[PDB]
Amino acid sequence: AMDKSAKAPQITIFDHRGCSRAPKESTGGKAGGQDDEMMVKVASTKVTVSESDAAKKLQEFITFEKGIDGPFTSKN
Amino acid sequence: AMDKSAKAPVITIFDHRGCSRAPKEYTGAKAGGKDDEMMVKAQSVKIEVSTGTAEGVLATSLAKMTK
Amino acid sequence: DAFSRVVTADSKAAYVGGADLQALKKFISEGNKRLDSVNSIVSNASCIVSDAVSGMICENPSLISPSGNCYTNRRMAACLRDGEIILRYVSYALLSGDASVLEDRCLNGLKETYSSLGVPANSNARAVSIMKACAVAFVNNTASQKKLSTPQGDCSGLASEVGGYFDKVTAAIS
Amino acid sequence: MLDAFSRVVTNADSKAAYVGGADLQALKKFISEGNKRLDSVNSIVSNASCIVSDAVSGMICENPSLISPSGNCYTNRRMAACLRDGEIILRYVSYALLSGDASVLEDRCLNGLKETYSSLGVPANSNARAVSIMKACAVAFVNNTASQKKLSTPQGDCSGLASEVGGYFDKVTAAIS
Ligand SMILES: *C(=C)C1=C(C)C(=O)N/C1=C\c1[nH]c(/C=C2\N=C(C[C@H]3NC(=O)C(C=C)=C3C)C(C)=C2CCC(=O)O)c(CCC(=O)O)c1C
Ligand SMILES: *C(=C)C1=C(C)C(=O)N/C1=C\c1[nH]c(/C=C2\N=C(C[C@H]3NC(=O)C(C=C)=C3C)C(C)=C2CCC(=O)O)c(CCC(=O)O)c1C
Ligand SMILES: *C(=C)C1=C(C)[C@@H](Cc2[nH]c(/C=C3N=C(/C=C4\NC(=O)[C@H](C)[C@H]4[C@@H](*)C)C(C)=C\3CCC(=O)O)c(CCC(=O)O)c2C)NC1=O
Ligand SMILES: *C(=C)C1=C(C)[C@@H](Cc2[nH]c(/C=C3N=C(/C=C4\NC(=O)[C@H](C)[C@H]4[C@@H](*)C)C(C)=C\3CCC(=O)O)c(CCC(=O)O)c2C)NC1=O
Ligand SMILES: *[C@@H](C)[C@H]1/C(=C/C2=NC(=C\c3[nH]c(C[C@H]4NC(=O)C(C=C)=C4C)c(C)c3CCC(=O)O)/C(CCC(=O)O)=C2C)NC(=O)[C@@H]1C
Ligand SMILES: *[C@@H](C)[C@H]1/C(=C/C2=NC(=C\c3[nH]c(C[C@H]4NC(=O)C(C=C)=C4C)c(C)c3CCC(=O)O)/C(CCC(=O)O)=C2C)NC(=O)[C@@H]1C
Ligand SMILES: *[C@H](C)[C@H]1/C(=C/C2=NC(=C\c3[nH]c(C[C@H]4NC(=O)C(C=C)=C4C)c(C)c3CCC(=O)O)/C(CCC(=O)O)=C2C)NC(=O)[C@@H]1C
Ligand SMILES: *[C@H](C)[C@H]1/C(=C/C2=NC(=C\c3[nH]c(C[C@H]4NC(=O)C(C=C)=C4C)c(C)c3CCC(=O)O)/C(CCC(=O)O)=C2C)NC(=O)[C@@H]1C
Ligand SMILES: [Cl-]
Ligand SMILES: [Mg+2]
Ligand SMILES: [Mg+2]
Image (cartoon, protein in one colour):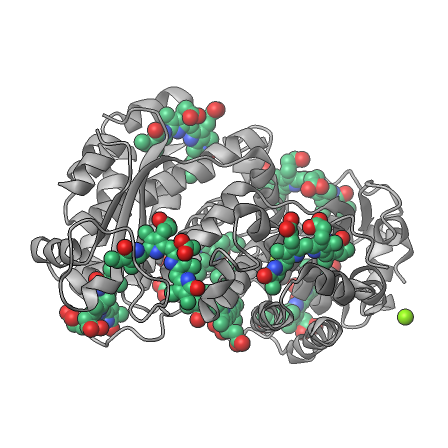
């Protein structure tokens, strides 16, 4: 059941082939190839949005503009 | 001078032609037309960015970079 | 196993790289394409959620009127948060190739909670449907912001799969 | 100068100022290209969060060392300050576009800014790329050549206003590079 904690999976996909920052976080050894420079990270973290951030979003939303993508569907 | 206050002019462009919520904030003279349903607001605001936003941009950047 | 522990038991993050990542890609279909598909959504999540909530509101501005469910910073924050939660569970369903966690941890009981709170189902359905459209375009790399160097090929199967996860959300809350 | 906004631009107070009705009718004939100009401002500021985040994250994907432990966006504190500065700059550019005049941008944002960045070690090459990406975003929002269905405005040619806003970003670039 949905447990009301506001926790959700948090994914980071690191395709860091060729990256000069050495990997140090894996725990299962080496593939002997480019998988050794890539990683999927999964955490379970609480999702939170501050009231101040929500105020910034409202000031954007209230004008009924849009991004490049999508049809314009507003009537206002 | 750049005064180090982190303030900037926040502009809100309210073109609310046809909107059922009545104008009230602007109390100057009326145009007698669609300009009475539209407004430019400006305000000096301290610009703030949260920890959460910063963490989100960090995660985006890590996921989009390669080398 | 490592992701299951995290998303349900083990508090610390799972770091799957190297040989563990090689193994992961043998247990999910189309592993390399699937990780590209997940990244195309997760790395663009901020714009997806913002565009979906903005579009829900621009189609129904009463949501931010004094009687609307997004009125006040507190409520707008909770709505933005919920869009991100939903998108996160859909993205994890695509990563894992399965809906089980999405169903158990995000959807089961959700409609009952929204009914009690008065969170409007038609509006919520629209936020979800805008997020769906965003995700399909990102998987197929046809959004306005494109990933430059993905190897070309057809990801329409993965795009159908993610669409089905969104449809589970819609069915559960509408 | 937009007199209604004089206290806003000097940071004299935090009071909102409003230009509607007859004052707005007159404003649009004081500035040029009035309706299109206000639509252009709206399309930029209403997308500010995304413009700034995409610019900063693009600066970073082009130069990942910015978020290495030695880079100037390392830690939430530094990242937030960088995103904040991107927004401050974008907002002063938006005021130059609203007013049709670069004065407030030059005088209240750019004057003294390079010397602050130099003292802090804020990398100018990286900052110039953040500004370049923000510029490209604004140009695309203003001169948006998609079909009517996809535009929030009546279709027409806003290439002149896009060139104008580009010039304001170029003043930022020249000041800080
Ligand atoms: C129509 C769009 C709307 C529907 C439908 C609805 O339910 N709400 C609608 C609009 C709406 N407006 C506000 C708030 C403000 N609008 C203005 C601008 C207008 N005031 C004027 O005097 C003129 C012209 C002369 C306007 C145009 C302003 C300044 C505000 C206050 C908020 C701000 O950001 O400064 C809201 C928000 C809730 C409310 O106050 O009613 C909504 C949703
Ligand atoms: C190359 C891109 C980079 C350049 C150039 C640079 O200056 N920094 C670069 C990358 C970079 N990586 C991190 C942090 C992390 N990277 C991973 C993933 C890798 N670790 C592994 O073990 C493997 C594969 C086996 C990887 C691929 C992880 C887990 C982190 C830690 C952070 C996290 O989100 O968990 C950074 C951040 C600063 C740092 O830690 O060096 C940077 C900028
Ligand atoms: C890292 C791999 C990396 C990036 C991150 C990305 C950064 C980048 N972005 C652009 C250009 C644009 N970004 C835009 C932003 C938005 N469009 C929207 O609809 C939303 C609301 C908003 C936030 C995402 C826009 C409008 C543009 C301009 C059009 C375009 O697509 O180019 C660039 C190009 C900059 C330039 O032209 O110099 C870059 C670099 N790219 C990466 O490589
Ligand atoms: C209010 C005036 C209003 C909106 C806001 C807007 C909402 C809307 N958006 C879409 C579709 C998409 N939005 C996308 C989002 C993004 N693309 C990017 O490149 C950036 C990073 C990100 C944030 C802006 C995308 C990818 C899509 C899909 C595009 C496509 O299919 O190619 C829609 C359409 C929803 C639907 O199809 O049901 C809408 C309505 N429109 C408004 O009027
Ligand atoms: C739909 C999603 C896309 C598309 C995807 C393709 N990706 C292909 C190959 C590919 N992708 C990666 C990166 C991926 N693997 C990982 O382990 C990680 C991160 C941990 C990621 C992000 C790799 C390694 C590969 C293999 C090739 C290579 O060495 O780069 C691919 C080719 C076919 C295939 O391998 O199955 C496709 C089609 N392509 C598209 O055009 C749409 C938009
Ligand atoms: C580039 C900017 C755009 C574009 C813009 C056009 N806008 C046009 C007309 C227009 N816009 C407004 C709204 C504006 N006036 C205000 O007072 C305020 C807010 C206070 C705003 C936001 C109005 C009232 C009008 C005129 C009436 C109308 O036609 O609705 C317009 C057409 C007229 C013209 O060409 O001058 C255009 C072209 N169009 C584009 O395609 C890009 C993306
Ligand atoms: C945004 C698109 C919506 C909208 C959403 C609102 N949700 C509110 C509260 C709320 N949401 C949840 C579900 C959330 N918590 C979880 O743990 C998970 C999954 C694991 C999810 C998806 C809960 C449990 C709650 C109540 C407790 C809380 O606030 O954290 C909410 C606040 C309502 C109120 O306080 O009055 C809103 C506004 N509202 C909309 O109008 C659109 C459709
Ligand atoms: C982002 C694209 C940059 C980046 C920016 C950083 N700026 C930092 C500090 C800082 N910035 C300013 C200028 C700002 N304040 C104002 O009042 C105005 C205009 C009116 C502007 C544009 C100041 C004065 C300061 C110092 C004081 C302060 O931060 O409040 C900064 C350091 C922050 C910290 O360590 O706390 C950063 C990281 N960094 C980058 O790498 C890119 C290029
Ligand atoms: Cl774009
Ligand atoms: Mg409009
Ligand atoms: Mg001067």
